[PDB]
Amino acid sequence: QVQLVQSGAAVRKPGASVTVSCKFAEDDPAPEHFIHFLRQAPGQQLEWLAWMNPTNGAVNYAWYLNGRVTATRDRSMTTAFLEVKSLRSDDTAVYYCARAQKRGRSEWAYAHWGQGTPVVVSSASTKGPSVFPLAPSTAALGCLVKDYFPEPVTVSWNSGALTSGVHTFPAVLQSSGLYSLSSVVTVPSSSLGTQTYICNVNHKPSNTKVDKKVEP
Amino acid sequence: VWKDADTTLFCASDAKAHETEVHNVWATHACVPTDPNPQEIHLENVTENFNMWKNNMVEQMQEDVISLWDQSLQPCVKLTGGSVIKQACPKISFDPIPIHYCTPAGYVILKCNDKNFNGTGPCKNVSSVQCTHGIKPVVSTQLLLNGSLAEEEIIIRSENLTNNAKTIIVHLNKSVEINCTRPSNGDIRKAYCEINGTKWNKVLKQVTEKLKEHFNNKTIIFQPPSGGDLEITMHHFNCRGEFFYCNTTQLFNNTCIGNETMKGCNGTITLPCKIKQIINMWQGTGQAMYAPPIDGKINCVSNITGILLTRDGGANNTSNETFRPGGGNIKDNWRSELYKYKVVQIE
Amino acid sequence: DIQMTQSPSSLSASLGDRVTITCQASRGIGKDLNWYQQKAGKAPKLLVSDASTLEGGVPSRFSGSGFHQNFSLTISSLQAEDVATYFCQQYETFGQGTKVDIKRTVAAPSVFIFPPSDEQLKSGTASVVCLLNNFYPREAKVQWKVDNALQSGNSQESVTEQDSKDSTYSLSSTLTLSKADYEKHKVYACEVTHQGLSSPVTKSFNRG
Ligand SMILES: *[C@@H]1O[C@H](CO)[C@@H](O[C@@H]2O[C@H](CO)[C@@H](O[C@@H]3O[C@H](CO)[C@@H](O)[C@H](O)[C@@H]3O)[C@H](O)[C@H]2NC(C)=O)[C@H](O)[C@H]1NC(C)=O
Ligand SMILES: *[C@@H]1O[C@H](CO)[C@@H](O)[C@H](O)[C@H]1NC(C)=O
Ligand SMILES: *[C@@H]1O[C@H](CO)[C@@H](O)[C@H](O)[C@H]1NC(C)=O
Ligand SMILES: *[C@@H]1O[C@H](CO)[C@@H](O)[C@H](O)[C@H]1NC(C)=O
Ligand SMILES: *[C@@H]1O[C@H](CO)[C@@H](O)[C@H](O)[C@H]1NC(C)=O
Ligand SMILES: *[C@@H]1O[C@H](CO)[C@@H](O)[C@H](O)[C@H]1NC(C)=O
Ligand SMILES: *[C@@H]1O[C@H](CO)[C@@H](O)[C@H](O)[C@H]1NC(C)=O
Ligand SMILES: *[C@@H]1O[C@H](CO)[C@@H](O)[C@H](O)[C@H]1NC(C)=O
Ligand SMILES: *[C@@H]1O[C@H](CO)[C@@H](O)[C@H](O)[C@H]1NC(C)=O
Ligand SMILES: *[C@@H]1O[C@H](CO)[C@@H](O)[C@H](O)[C@H]1NC(C)=O
Ligand SMILES: *[C@@H]1O[C@H](CO)[C@@H](O)[C@H](O)[C@H]1NC(C)=O
Ligand SMILES: *[C@@H]1O[C@H](CO)[C@@H](O)[C@H](O)[C@H]1NC(C)=O
Ligand SMILES: *[C@@H]1O[C@H](CO)[C@@H](O)[C@H](O)[C@H]1NC(C)=O
Ligand code: NA
Ligand code: NA
Ligand code: NA
């Protein structure tokens, strides 16, 4: 049940195209299992997109893709490629490739999966987060990490020394098209006044760095 | 008493020993002569299960056809992996002949005779034979050529009709001629196939109605292939040794299938074809290059006796089903002729 | 064309409990059904193919059964690592999924409210945050009132995955309104409803 290897995360504007590649074999009998492509949007159901026969390039695309999708393989027939054209916002999802096991005759039983390729379709431009304090009143405190694009941000406290009782929530997508999240932690109410609390925020996509002290 | 079993079959044929035609040559050394007076025995009150989709006779025919092509249709250049083989590539004489498949001693072939048997499940009218009928090893895509016809109604075969990853074989009960020509004397590679439009659209209409029975009276739509190599996006076959590729867009033309009295639905349908020198081998072994076509009129008149289809996937399709020409692999061509046979061991 | 009805949509059980999920098909499908497990942030993993064949490597506690129209997936003796969403598949169609959770003793949420920072108001926007910490079960209700006026449509929330050790959840709700709208009203309140509470809880503050 080896993992399939997919290309990295992508950001596209509406109208543009994206290609997701999936290496399913090595370049070194029996019939080859088709390669399947599926996607899963944030907090949505898994959705089948297509299969592709690596032997002859035969394909089958879900009727609801309206011919916007194309699946191909390379000459050595070891890497599959899924191109999605005319992207729209609701194409935003993690895209997977998948395949049945060679030893089996269960063509839909996906023993092999890629790690997933996040694809984000938005009109929004890259932007670092603003970081605001969530001042304390055990007492709770935290940082509001607001108005960034695209995902992800990373958050630590006191440069990693503080890990106990930290909750860093999943990001939500705001109506402005920018993401926002919060990171909270609970501490003794005596800590305040002597113990310094600082959330450290990184946003690789913008090479942005923020360190915010949180105090009452 | 007996039981389903796999064994090494042998072939029989009426090949001409003096002939240079390549099927004749292969069969003269690989097969025995036909049995003049073959024996067939109805097995009264016997019911038997068949499965055309898991039938080892098909694998054996495949090996034979691959072997025939390997020794008869040598390309000038063969490109496999990193190996480049440059050999000699003389023009040949090529015209498939019927091959019968026969069981050895201790074994026998059971044959399903139910008029509308669909390839899977019980047969009520069963007989035993020593050999199959004569099957031409015609290699083609999309359209099945020069095959045998369903006895009564048009028949839809599939391991699972609801499974979009499974090939559908339509078995016609009346053949439609396709007349493919590369004229002499303007590109030498340019060719075309003519088909009687009146005749073809009548048949295709019957096919849609047949599919309606299997898909809950839903709207049935035909479309061109969605993609793939040219061997499968086009009707691909070998005529007189030359490799033809024909565009079938016009054969699957919903306009004329709505029964709508419409202009041009009658009359001759002319498909554009090309003869290619550089091809992908159906045997699965990469690219091969051949020499340019022979001079003069190259003509093949074939019977369309069947159609391979793939059905569009996607859940909640609700209102319709869409079918595109082409499906599966060349083994399925043999399955369409071997569907009614299976081998058993006499115990 | 096929329709798979998967049930229940969510369940909770103690470690070592027996859990079963069902999928009903609108039409006979023989044994052409597979079962998957999917954990948060990960690709699905095949558990069972052809209704009842356990896939190599999968722990022996898992089993599938059924044919025709009635199919089940069972975990004998639920384990911590089994927290996941499970779903059935019939060709390209998937069941709606079942979120398995680990049952612990009921726990009310510690509620906290955070006013926006002076820093943020300079930008013309105001984010008010209500936190619910370490509660169970996950189902909870949060409503915002601004001067006793039920706030609707300007709210977003986020929930954590079930915590490894204490089997609890945390939730945040964030209320977004203009700076002007914020400097208009005095009292901002977070009203919470949860099973571990005899009655709803309200945390609030005066803008000043
Ligand atoms: C679909 O099949 C499932 C199993 O694959 C069926 O589940 C079972 O349903 C019966 C009642 O119809 C339950 O009866 C049980 O009997 C045992 C004794 O053998 C007893 O220990 C139980 O307390 C119960 O009384 C059975 O629990 C249940 N199995 C479960 C829930 O795991 C189901 O009935 C079928 N549904 C249909 C056909 O709609
Ligand atoms: C088959 O059964 C019928 C009646 O069911 C009987 O008349 C016939 O003789 C049987 N087959 C034989 C005797 O071979
Ligand atoms: C063929 O007939 C059998 C009847 O035993 C049925 O089970 C099967 O679904 C049929 N297949 C098609 C493609 O009609
Ligand atoms: C062929 O089969 C169709 C039904 O699929 C039927 O309507 C038609 O009459 C048949 N043709 C002949 C010549 O039997
Ligand atoms: C096949 O087509 C050629 C070229 O149009 C024509 O000369 C010939 O008569 C046709 N043969 C038949 C049997 O229709
Ligand atoms: C095509 O076939 C139809 C149906 O049999 C026939 O009426 C018509 O004459 C044919 N057209 C020709 C032979 O050109
Ligand atoms: C389809 O249409 C026919 C009429 O031609 C009707 O008798 C039949 O019940 C319909 N339903 C299905 C599922 O085929
Ligand atoms: C077939 O012809 C149509 C129109 O002539 C064209 O649009 C289509 O691309 C062709 N198909 C192939 C596979 O060349
Ligand atoms: C020929 O085509 C017309 C539609 O354009 C149709 O109405 C007619 O029935 C067709 N075939 C015949 C008359 O044999
Ligand atoms: C379908 O056939 C009609 C003739 O009835 C023809 O005019 C039209 O070009 C065809 N539709 C296509 C090629 O999409
Ligand atoms: C089909 O059979 C005819 C008659 O034997 C032959 O002339 C023709 O070339 C064959 N077609 C193919 C594609 O083999
Ligand atoms: C094509 O079919 C006709 C009858 O429909 C037959 O006369 C002819 O021999 C067939 N050609 C073959 C089988 O190659
Ligand atoms: C597929 O065909 C089998 C027969 O081999 C049948 O039992 C099963 O119901 C079919 N599957 C579906 C999903 O219809
Ligand atoms: Na988006
Ligand atoms: Na056999
Ligand atoms: Na091939």
Image: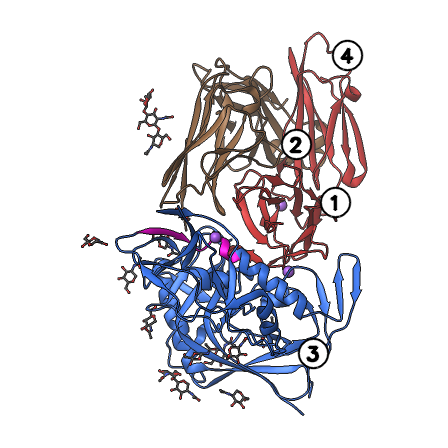
Residue to which mark 4 is pinned: A195
Q: What amino acid type is highlighted by mark number 4?
A: Gln
- Chain coloured brown in the rendered structure: C
Question: Which of the two labelled residues, at mark 1 and mark 4, occupies the earlier sequence position?
Answer: 1
Q: Quadrant of residue A156?
A: top right
- For label 1, count other residues whose C-alpha is less than 10 Å away and answer few (under 14), some (14-19) or many (20+): some
Asked whether B241 falls inside the magenta stretch, the response is no
Image coloring type: by chain
| Residue at the extreme bottom of the image, as rendered | B185
Q: Where residue B93 appears, x then y in whole percent?
A: 63, 79
Write the start and end of the magenta stretch as one range: B47-58
Task: Identify the chain drawn in blue.
Answer: B
Disc 3 beta carbon < 8 A from ligand 11? Answer: no
Task: Say what secondary structure mark 3 lies in.
Answer: loop
Is B294 situated left or right of A211 in this image? left
Is the C-beta of the residue carrying label 2 under 8 Å from the nearest atom of ligand 14?
A: no
Q: Give the residue number, with chain letter if any, for mark 1.
A: A126
The residue at 57%/76% (across/down) is B95
> Which residue is rendered at x = 42% and y = 66% of the image?
B171
Question: Do badges 3 and 2 share one subunit?
Answer: no
How far apart marks 1 and 4 lie (CA) works out to 35 Å
Instruction: Judge whether A55 appears above or below A175 on screen.
Output: below
